Image (cartoon, coloured by chain):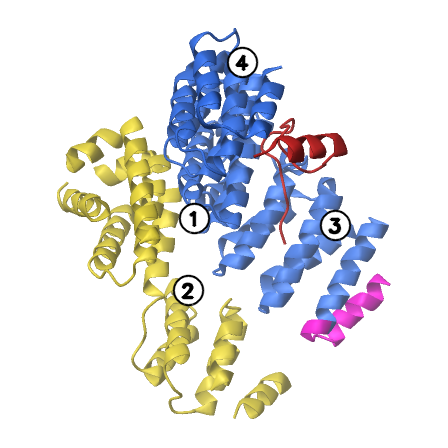
Chain colours: A yellow, B blue, C red
Amino acid sequence: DLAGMFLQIFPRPVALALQQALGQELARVVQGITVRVLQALATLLSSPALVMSMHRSHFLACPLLRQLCQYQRCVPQDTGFSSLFLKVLLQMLQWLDSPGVEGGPLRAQLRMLASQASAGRRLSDVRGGLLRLAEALAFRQDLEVVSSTVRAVIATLRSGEQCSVEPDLISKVLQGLIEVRSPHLEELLTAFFSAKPVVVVSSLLLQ
Amino acid sequence: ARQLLQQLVTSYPSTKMVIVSLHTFTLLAASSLVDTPKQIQLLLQYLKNDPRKAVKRLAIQDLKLLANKTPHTWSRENIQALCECALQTPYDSLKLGMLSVLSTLSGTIAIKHYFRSSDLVKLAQECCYHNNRGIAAHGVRVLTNITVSCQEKDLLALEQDAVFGLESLLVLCSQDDSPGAQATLKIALNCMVKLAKGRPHLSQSVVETLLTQLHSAQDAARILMCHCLAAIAMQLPVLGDGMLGDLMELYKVIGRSATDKQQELLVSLATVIFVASQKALSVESKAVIKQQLESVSNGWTVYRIARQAS
Amino acid sequence: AAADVSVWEENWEDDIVQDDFNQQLRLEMER
């Protein structure tokens, strides 16, 4: 069955048939089995491994994860598939974070998928998130956390309205981000000044 | 002029002014070809540091121009910096641009100058399984170029990574029937042809992937993979016998409902039938003549198939 | 920002060049 299918693939043409079936399902859905295989994979991940076999055979696992993510992107309103996909991605991240496994394309692909999943959600408090960014940038540590929080702030500014101004706070955050040289500076400035900006920019330039 | 352009980029850092100045500096370096290494270093500095997406995009275009013009002048450090930039950027358009530059470089002698599991191979493996089809095409092109150009035995583990990435890209691009997907499909099939030439022991797996994917692909995709099979079987005709059954079956099922776009598919299928046939045809010939006479009033299709037969 | 490449470099089906003889033959015999 699908659990036996997984235990036959990773520990080869049957995986090709599975890929063809997933592509057919994707074409059918975009024109108008994925949930079954995802649930089988989740239940197999619950029990004890398979992740190490997917690591040694990433050329099998990574196309499957790509197909599942494209399914998720095609129909994002089908909640339950996306939550379970995020759950299994985090489960694999937990199971692959050990130092002994060293690098691997599979880890990077899963981390990219997790970051993509976490970027499509809002954040409640603009002031709270900006203060979080202020002290996180004060320590200059947890750069992945910094990037995720900036992405959340950008999404918040995209959807939400303008919170309290706090020009000193915003100037300090901008100066810190310039110092750390984050790639999200341009997006942050666009989102911020879409909503005083001249005084902030002039003060930053003078310093 | 170089000193003046440096003074301009530092003293007029507007988006328009810095873009025009950096492009002019790149063209001057290309024409003079003595400042070209430090011009590449400057462009990589602007790509890494400058946060403006427009400036990064210009830097990508200029580095692609320099890669096309003077790939030999690229150092290992330059390619390492470009790979690091591609690795740690969050934006997909920029990543696609840098991978276009790197795929241009990998097709040249710069890959030989670049040489283990380095940042380039790590990036290429990461990119060939990307959600973005263009990034996947560029990554798998880089992998194919490394595999066929470098026979070093320390990096034969990515030989199958290249094969499986090409196959997954086939599965991704076959159903879409969109011009961008068709472009990525052409890139993947060109890479497969190149890989079949460079590493003939992988030819059987490539042919098997193409044959299995033929039965579950759209008509335009089917035509492109028929061209790929024709190329591989022209260079390596031993594989022709193994592909005749699938091709003949698909020829039978296509000819029953061949309305408008299947005429190109018909000539492509007949072309691979004739190419893959080392010897003559007895029953396959009867099948082809029957398929032509049953429905095909299109004389042009018959003429092109006869051209291929002769 | 793109580039074009051909899968098969001796494929006779490419319409990159159209010659008069094949033009009238096609227009004369295609249905």
The subunit letter for the residue under badge 1 reads B
Q: Residues within 10 Å of mark 3 (few under 14, many from 20)?
A: some
Give the spatial CA distance, label 4 vs label 3. Answer: 45 Å
Seen from the viewer's position, the closer of residues C17 and A30 is C17
Picture disc at residue A143: 2
Please state the chain letter of the residue tagged with numbered disc 4 in the rendered image. B
Q: Are marks 4 and 1 in contact (CB under 8 Å)?
A: no
Residue at the location (51% across, 37% down)? B188
In front: label 4 or label 1: 4
- The earlier-in-sequence mark between 1 and 3 is 3
* Label 1 and label 3 in one chain: yes
Give the image location of residue A17, x and y in percent. 29, 32
Q: Is the residue under label 2 in contact with that under label 4 (CB below 8 Å)?
A: no
CA distance for labels 4 and 2: 54 Å
**In the foreground, B306 or A194:** B306
Residues drawn in magenta: B1-16
Tell me the amino acid under the disc marked 2: Leu
Q: Which of the numbered marks, if any, corresponds to residue B237?
A: 4
Dot 1 falls on a residue whose secondary structure is loop
- Name the image quarter holding the N terminus of chain B: bottom right
Residue B225 point in image, percent of width and height: 49, 31
What's under tag 4, amino acid-wise? Pro
**Residue at 69% across / 38% down in the picture?**
C16
SS type, badge 3: helix
Q: CA distance from mark 2 to mark 3?
A: 32 Å
